[PDB]
Amino acid sequence: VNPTVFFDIAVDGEPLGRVSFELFADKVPKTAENFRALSTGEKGFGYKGSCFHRIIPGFMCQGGDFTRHNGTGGKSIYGEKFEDENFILKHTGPGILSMANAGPNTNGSQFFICTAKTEWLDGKHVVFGKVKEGMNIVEAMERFGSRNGKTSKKITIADCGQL
Image (tube, rainbow, N blue to C red; front, side):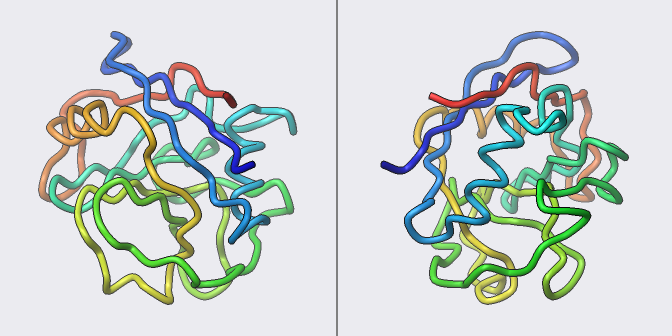
């Protein structure tokens, strides 16, 4: 059965809500397992305490950089990077969960939640999940963003894990 993880989001330290994701381990098992193990911190590191450093309304909320907190760091459980598993799944609309990267086969820990349809990233970013509950909480994160991505308040993952 496809695993389910959750984020407890905080805005400048104040609780905001819970976002839960369905990870399509059946279709992208390696990518979904990385994200799952970073949400539980079972490898010693992960997402708990990291932030959403780049939020663009109408585009996507991006986070997952738990070593440099600005988009220049992060690492997977398999090493500093790992390959593109497949591009079966498409960026069909809001709620999609896809992996960020700096070129072919450079996936680490940085993901982005689509707040819109982003079909131009098909074949370039691996889709591996979707928001299951708390899409309202993601839309509340979006309003603390800006056209260039700098957030007006600190959006953090106060807690994460598996359900």
